[PDB]
DNA sequence: ATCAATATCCACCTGCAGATTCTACCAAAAGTGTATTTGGAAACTGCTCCATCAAAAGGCATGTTCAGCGGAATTCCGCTGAACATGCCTTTTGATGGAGCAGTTTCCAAATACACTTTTGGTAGAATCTGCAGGTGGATATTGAT
DNA sequence: ATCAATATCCACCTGCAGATTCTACCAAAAGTGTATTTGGAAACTGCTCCATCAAAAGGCATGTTCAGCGGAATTCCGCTGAACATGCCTTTTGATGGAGCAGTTTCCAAATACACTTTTGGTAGAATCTGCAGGTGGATATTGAT
């Protein structure tokens, strides 16, 4: 089990909860903020 | 004891017989040897360790942000607040080189810019010039000195024609003081000779004097010093502010060799926005 | 005094540091070029990745000792 | 002018935009130690007789640093006193907490990952820092062999040391000062985009 | 509260400020100015408040004279406003030396 | 009896006497014939208070406070060519647009 | 030690646009801008030209304050006397 | 010095129209006027009597001085009141 | 029998008169002018030769000063001509009336 | 009779062109005569009261050079 | 036998000391340390006449006569203001032409 | 028949700097008027400040501040310098 | 571009006004010791006055946006200076008279000093009160989108 | 044309603030009276510079053509008055430090004044060369016709 299935399915969504704390600037418009973190792939 | 301390000192890649005395740590004088390497700058006197005790660290590059880069030499920026110690010893690297200015007061309130050779492994310093924070007495630069291994290929000059660029990259004029110069007496004169003739070839004339300070940031109190360092650049203002001329131009035809010591005016900002009102 | 002079000085040692979220990506954005096409230099991606917060952790020495100096006055 | 290549090992890679960098000395240079030459080769004089376990050249250079961090940091008022510090078995509380080359402010958030070989590797200590061995265990393993040499080392100069030195309102302003902590974890967790790649990426071949 | 033509509240302001008699540049930044253009000449001197008062009325008389003759220059130039060229013209044939 | 007040001019002829002596340099000053001068400092100083009877004729308010004093000197052209050199304090400008 | 007293030797040449009040003490209408920098320069020039010979009067007088009397004498010989204020 | 022209400009304002009132700083204004015009006439009168190789001051060179430094109509009224008061001093010994 | 370009001989006229230095007005009409303008103040004066010489170089100095500043006001007015209005306005803003 | 017309338009044409003018508009002549008579009377009045003082009923060069030294237009050379 | 020109000066000490006694709004004047002033005019008549023959040789006339004085007594930048109130007799006007008139029309 | 000018002194100072010179008497009068009225200028303003500084002996240091005060800058600096060396070399009365 | 037509730069020629030495002379002063009388250099110590410094109230300085108009460019289009040239008009020159400028000697008169009173004008203790500056509501111009 | 809310002038009451008029010390200059001194007033004498007065020529005067030129107009556009919402730093009144002014007092270097006594810098003639002012003339630099 440690060789077959774990290696991506536990890694498919960890990279996409950034999109609730890139919104930490609101609480300038900068909605499409692609400065630092959106292009790390 | 204003003479050089001991009989042989290497500075990284080459030995330098130093010029003057520095406030070096005194207790290393009874053994006959002092040596010092490039990027740690922590002082020793015997090669018994840094033959492989520079496996203390893998520092290849100083923490100055390399703010220009070219085909041949780069340079960077140190402030005295984000670092406290190796910013300090670079002066004591060369207080044995510099003739007058030494430390009693701590060297923190000065920004510190240092010129540097590209290298195959880690890029090595050649010069240093020291801008203060804002408006000491004008005086846009301070102590400027090049490492004595590496002069006469013309690299000691292009950093005193970087120095005037960060004055109208902040949009106020500036110029050095007197303090003393017989060691480089004609050197800043050489650039202040050709800082004007290389950019008096375009004017569509009837041009005044003070806009030169607005365009080359070389001030009003020394344009006339350079208008008399070389030939007659007057006999026209007689009821108003000074006027400048041109002549037979045996200068720009000699401006094809000894011209390429330039900079590409294309890189980053240099404003310190904070105040840090210093008192001690 | 304990609020006043101790206010802002934890930002100019971070005035060099907006650079952490601008040090990092274009050399991870240049080593993705190394895996888009056997594990020779593929080890060293993490050893510059783990240095992300490492000085911010050294700032976390300071940016939680300054919070730990909330009680230096009787009000805060 | 031939001493170059014994201390000129290393590698180099060029820039991508500009070489931006920021550090201090004591987090770039790493360690803090210092030796003589007459303790380099003949303080370990007859260690050839009885070198069952570890005896190399480059393993005793780290623990020569850590003990003198007690004096200049934990007792700063100790400026000239010859009756200076407690003995090696009496300074046992000075090993559970210390600051040797700023260790525990470097080793406080280091166990949340547990990399498969071993955890934290920095680019700001040199290349060979693992079998450069952990001093977690070597106080109670070979800690006593360096103490009595140190216990006579400092007292010939007793108060300064023989290596060189340096001769002679609340409202509406401090509120973003705690709002610079919503970066509480947001750098390493998306360093953990790919810092969970490596514990299983390194070993794909072991079907064969 | 609809706005009238652009200009007449400025002209009522010039008649107000002309018929009035107060001092116009605010005093303590001007005191800071005369200090920190004074101590560059020689190090720390002190003042007394009547002397800096005389400074500010002297300089306001001088540059209101400079503005009145550059206004006559601007009305000479078949223009209604002032520029840089008429102000250094007016200071020029004033003979500032 | 008293040398000023017998003479019908009431400024002090005694105090004008040594002020020539402490200042002039031909080292002898005529005694009685400095009186001929300080007629004039009476006659001028009348001729800036006597046409400062304008305010008591038009400017309605009786004790004469120093912006009133800017309605005679430059403004009244006969006195202008004796006081260009003086710029009076806190007075202002005579009105014109 | 202390060795130097506080100095705010910085950008004080920005006074205010009260030049847009004293312009309107003069008879001038709308002002067209971009003159504020050289009128601040000329205010700096005339002020330094009066204060430096005033402080030569003070340093001649063996004092280290200025007073109203020697500054009104200073601008009196400078070419235009401030009048009735000392 | 420790001197003034205060009470004399009080009395001249009182010998003209008695209604108005001398104010606080206006006496310094008028004092500066009378001291400045006196210093003016004194330096040009002394220089006149100097450059004509003469060795005293009299009535007539300060008469020519106050004619020399004024607008015309005020000079004529000034020299008239000057001659009037000097001859009224000369009438009685 | 050749007409030059208009105005280009004016520039060599001004170079010719500017390089030379001699007293350019002619002396005896000026001498009659100064005599029967001195007649009005008291009759029957006589002059000295160096005195009238001082008068003529004084008046060409003052005249050449007023011509250069009215020329500079003229070229301020985007105008290569000098007219009544610019000589009297330059006359005003150099101060004297 | 008048003799202020004794100075003529080539003469003040030359006196203007010494300053550096190109064009001369054809009615500046009468007021340049006016400004010359104004300056000339303002200097000869204090010169004549200088000579009326010293009991010599001629002027000299010394009193007119002292007169120009009075009124802010100090000539040199002749005293 | 040195007649009081012995501070390296070559102007008459006796006549300047009698002339300060002549001018003398005050009473007394320091007969030894009034030497300070007539050396001070030795600067700016020489630094007036050293720039006189500074370019009087550029016109190649060896006896230097009245016009070339003004051709840089009023063109020397700082000796202008010490002589601005003077208009020296028959010494000419500097060669200056504004370049708005020279436009090749 | 007696009158005194500054002819021979100005002749000697400028032949002594530049030997290849000659002087017209008109230019000699122009320099005589120059030196005379700048003399009287220093005299009157020096005497005025020494008057109102509660003082009667016309000493050297007030003419030093006077020559600093009315002469323009750079020439005032060189002037006060050679005046300082002049009263230095006169104090040694050897 | 390619020459006619000016003309200024350079060089050489004599005439002459004139600067430069010179030098005697010489009346007039710098310059010399000798007391010397006092103004000044300096130093005492009291103390008025400047200078940092702060807390809260609030007018006012910065920024930003919008409407529009004054600046400016470019144009056409009468007109008045500039440029020659001839005609004349008074100049610029040398040559003979005459009232003031500039020395002198004496006559008296007015200013020095010096002191003896003595009114008078600066200072402040201090009444006083009214002449202002300021609010505040009652009559009257203010100059447009509609 | 026209009403629109805005800004302006005026009688009326109110705190406050510095004139202003004694009280009087009081200190100190000023009127007044001598004695003698040196400087101005007037008269003179004579040596001049100022006024005035005739015959060659260059610079003014009054022209006529023509083209650079100013003036008028008209439209286009960026950049400036005006408003409003908001930050900020003035903005006045205490408050303690602390010191540099300032009056006084003091002893002493030194500029005035004085008879003499020597050189020494004006001056006035005067040789006398010479520097340059003017003129003439040859060649390269400059400008307009085509």
Image (cartoon, coloured by chain):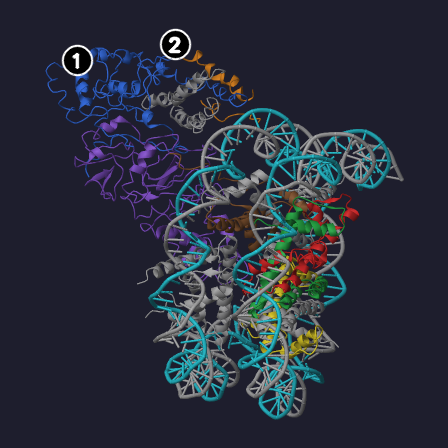
Chain colours: A orange, B purple, D blue, F red, G brown, H green, I yellow, M cyan
**Disc 2 and disc 1: Cα gap in Å?**
41 Å
Instruction: Tell me the quarter of the picture where residue D158 sits.
Output: top left
Q: Position of residue H52 (x, y in %)?
A: 57, 71
Mark yes or no: residue C34 visible: yes
Q: Residues within 10 Å of mark 2 (few under 14, many from 20)?
A: few
Q: On the rendered structure, is M3 left or right of G24?
A: left
Q: Residues within 10 Å of mark 1 (few under 14, many from 20)?
A: few
Whether residue B265 is situated above or below residue F41 in the rendered picture: above
Mark yes or no: residue D189 visible: no
Number of disc labels:
2
Whether residue H8 is situated above or below residue H42 in the rendered picture: above
Q: On the rendered structure, is M120 left or right of B77?
A: right
- Determine whether the residue tagged by mark 1 lies in a helix, strand or loop: loop
Q: Which residue is nearer to you in this view: F16 or G57?
A: F16
Q: On the rendered structure, is M92 left or right of C45?
A: right
Q: Position of residue D88 (x, y in %)?
A: 21, 13
Q: Which residue is nearer to you in this view: F49 or M92?
A: F49
Q: Which residue is nearer to you in this view: A37 or B191?
A: B191
What residue is disc 1 on?
D53
What residue is disc 2 on?
A4
Quarter of the figure with the N terminus of chain A: top left
Q: Position of residue G50 (x, y in %)?
A: 54, 50
Q: Chain of mark 2?
A: A
Quarter of the figure with the C terminus of chain A: top left
- Label drawn at residue F4: none
- Of marks 2 and 1, the one in the foreground: 1
Whether residue F73 is situated above or below residue B272 in the rendered picture: below
Whether residue M90 is situated above or below residue B218 in the rendered picture: below
Q: Chain of mark 1?
A: D
């Amino acid at each position: 089990l440690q060789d077959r299935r774990e290696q991506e399915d536990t890694f498919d969504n960890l990279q996409q909860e950034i999109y609730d704390k890139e919104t930490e600037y609101f609480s300038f418009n900068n909605n499409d903020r692609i400065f630092s973190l959106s292009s790390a792939t | 004891a204003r003479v050089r301390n001991l009989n042989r000192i290497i500075m990284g890649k080459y030995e330098i017989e130093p010029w003057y005395f520095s406030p070096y740590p005194i207790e290393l004088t009874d053994e006959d040897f002092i040596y010092i390497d490039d990027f740690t700058l922590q002082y020793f006197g015997s090669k018994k360790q840094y033959e492989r005790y520079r496996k203390k660290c893998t520092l290849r590059h100083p923490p100055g942000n390399e703010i220009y880069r070219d085909d041949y030499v780069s340079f960077f920026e140190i402030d005295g607040r984000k670092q406290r110690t190796w910013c300090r010893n670079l002066c004591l690297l060369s207080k044995l080189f510099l003739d007058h200015k030494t430390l009693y007061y701590d060297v923190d309130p000065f920004l510190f810019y240092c010129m540097t050779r590209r290298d195959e492994l880690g890029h090595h310093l050649v010069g240093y010039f020291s801008k203060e924070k804002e408006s000491a007495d004008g005086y846009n630069v301070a102590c400027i000195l090049t490492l004595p291994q590496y002069q006469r290929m013309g690299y000691g000059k292009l950093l005193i024609e970087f120095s005037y660029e960060l004055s109208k990259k902040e949009n106020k004029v500036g110029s050095p003081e007197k303090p003393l110069s017989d060691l480089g007496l004609l050197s800043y004169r050489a650039y202040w000779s050709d800082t004007l003739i290389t950019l008096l070839v375009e004017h569509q004339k009837e041009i005044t004097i003070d806009e030169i300070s607005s365009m080359t940031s070389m001030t009003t109190t020394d344009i006339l010093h350079t208008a008399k360092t070389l030939n007659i650049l007057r006999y026209y203002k007689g009821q108003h502010i000074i006027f400048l001329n041109e002549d037979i131009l045996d200068r720009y035809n000699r401006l094809k060799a000894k011209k390429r010591r330039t900079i590409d005016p294309n890189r980053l900002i240099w404003k310190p926005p904070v105040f840090t009102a210093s008192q001690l | 005094m304990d609020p006043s002079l101790v206010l802002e000085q934890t930002i100019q040692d971070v005035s060099n540091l907006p650079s952490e979220f601008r040090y990092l990506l274009e050399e991870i954005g240049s080593n993705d070029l190394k895996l888009i096409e056997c594990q020779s230099l593929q080890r060293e991606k993490c050893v510059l990745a783990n240095t992300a917060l490492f000085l911010i952790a050294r700032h976390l020495n300071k940016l939680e000792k300054n919070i730990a100096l909330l009680e230096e006055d009787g009000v805060l | 002018w031939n001493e170059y290549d014994k201390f000129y090992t290393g590698s180099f890679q060029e820039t991508t935009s500009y070489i931006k960098f920021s550090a201090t000395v004591e987090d770039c240079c790493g360690t803090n130690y210092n030796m003589d030459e007459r303790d380099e080769t003949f303080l370990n004089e007859q260690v050839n007789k009885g070198s069952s376990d570890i005896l190399t050249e480059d393993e005793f250079e780290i623990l020569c640093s850590s003990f003198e961090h007690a004096i200049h940091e934990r007792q700063p008022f100790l400026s000239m006193d010859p009756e200076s510090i407690l003995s090696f078995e009496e300074l046992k509380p000075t090993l559970i907490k210390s600051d040797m080359a700023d260790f525990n402010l470097r080793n406080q958030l280091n166990h949340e990952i547990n990399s498969h070989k071993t955890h934290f590797i920095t680019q700001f200590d040199p290349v060979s820092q693992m079998n450069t061995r952990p001093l977690i265990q070597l106080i109670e393993k070979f800690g006593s062999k360096i103490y009595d040499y140190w216990r006579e080392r400092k007292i010939e100069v007793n108060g300064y040391e023989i290596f060189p030195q340096l001769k002679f309102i609340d409202i509406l302003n401090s509120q973003r000062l705690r709002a610079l902590h919503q970066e509480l974890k947001n750098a390493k967790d998306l360093a953990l985009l790919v810092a969970k790649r490596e514990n299983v990426s390194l070993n794909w071949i072991n079907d064969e | 509260p609809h706005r009238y033509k652009p200009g007449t509240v400025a002209l009522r302001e010039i008649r107000r400020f002309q018929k009035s008699t107060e001092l116009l540049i605010r005093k303590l930044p001007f005191q800071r100015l005369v200090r920190e253009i004074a101590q560059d000449f020689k190090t720390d001197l002190r003042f007394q408040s009547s002397a800096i008062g005389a400074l500010q009325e002297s300089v306001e008389a001088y540059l209101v004279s400079l503005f009145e003759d550059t206004n006559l220059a601007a009305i000479h130039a078949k223009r209604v406003t002032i520029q840089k060229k008429d102000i250094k013209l007016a200071r020029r044939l004033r003979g500032e030396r | 009896q008293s040398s000023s007040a017998r003479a019908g001019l009431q400024f002090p002829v005694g105090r004008i006497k040594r002020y020539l002596k402490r200042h002039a340099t031909g080292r002898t000053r005529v005694g009685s014939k400095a009186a001929i001068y300080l007629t004039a400092v009476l006659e001028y100083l009348t001729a800036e208070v006597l046409e400062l009877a304008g305010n008591a004729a038009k400017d309605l308010k009786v004790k004469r406070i120093t912006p009133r004093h800017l309605q005679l000197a430059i403004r009244g052209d006969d006195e202008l060519d004796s006081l260009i050199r003086a710029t009076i304090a806190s007075g202002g400008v005579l009105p014109h647009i | 030690k202390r060795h130097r007293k506080i100095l705010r030797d910085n950008i004080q040449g920005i006074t205010k646009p009260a030049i847009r009040r004293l312009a309107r003490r003069g008879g001038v209408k709308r002002i067209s801008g971009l003159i504020y920098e050289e009128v601040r320069a000329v205010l700096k020039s005339f002020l330094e030209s009066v204060i430096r010979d005033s402080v030569t009067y003070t340093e001649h007088a063996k004092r280290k304050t200025v007073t109203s009397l020697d500054v009104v004498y200073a601008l009196k010989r400078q070419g235009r006397t401030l009048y009735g204020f000392g | 010095r420790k001197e003034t022209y205060s009470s004399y400009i009080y009395k001249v304002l009182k010998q003209t129209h008695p209604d108005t009132g001398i104010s606080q700083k206006s006496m310094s204004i008028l004092n500066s006027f009378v001291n400045d015009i006196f210093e003016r006439i004194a330096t040009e009168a002394s220089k006149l009597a100097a450059y004509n190789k003469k060795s005293t001051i009299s009535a007539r060179e300060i008469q020519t001085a106050v004619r020399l430094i004024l607008p015309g109509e005020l000079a004529k009224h000034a020299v008239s009141e000057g001659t009037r008061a000097v001859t009224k001093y000369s009438s009685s010994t």
